Image 1 (cartoon, each protein chain N blue to C red):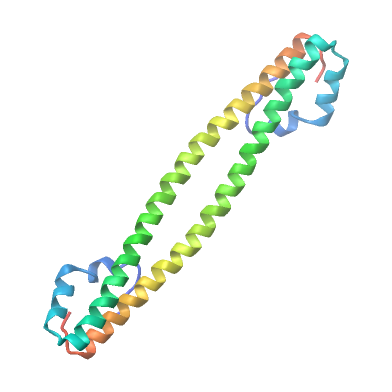
Image 2 (cartoon, one colour; image 1 turned 45 degrees about the vertical axis):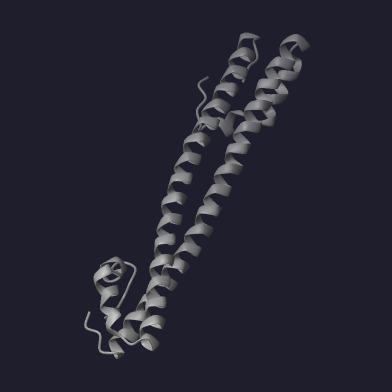
Length: 88
Length: 88
C-alpha cells in the first residue's frame, strides 16, 4: 500500500485508525503515534497552504491598489506639467 | 499622454523629471512632489511584489517538505501495521 500526497486523505481515516485498536499496546501505541503525527502535520500543511493563498490574494489586491494610485499621481504630475507647456 | 502600469517606467524617467526644472517654483515643486511620490509608491509596489513572490516560493518549498514528511510518517505507520497483520 503506497501512500502519496494525493491519496493521503483516503487512507488516513477514522475507519483505518480504529483497526489499530486490536494490536497489543507495545505495537499499537507506536503505530498510532505515527498515524496521529502524520495527520497533524498534513492538516497543518493544509492550514498553512490555505492561509498562504489568502494572504497572497489579499496582498495582491492591495498592491494593485498601490500601483493604481502611483499611476494616478504620475498622471496628475504629467497633466499639470503639460498645462504649463512642458514638452514630454 | 495616458499613463498605465505598463508604460509607467517609460515615462517616469530622469529625462522627464529634468524637464520640470524650467518651471517657476510655484508650479515646479507641486509637480515634482507628485512625480516623486508616484515613483516612490511604484518602486515600493515593485519591492512588495518581488518580496511576496520570494516569500511565497520559500513557503511552498517548506510546505512541500512538510507534506513529504507527513506522507512518510503515514507510510511508516501503515507499513508497521501491515507487518502486524492489520487488514486495511
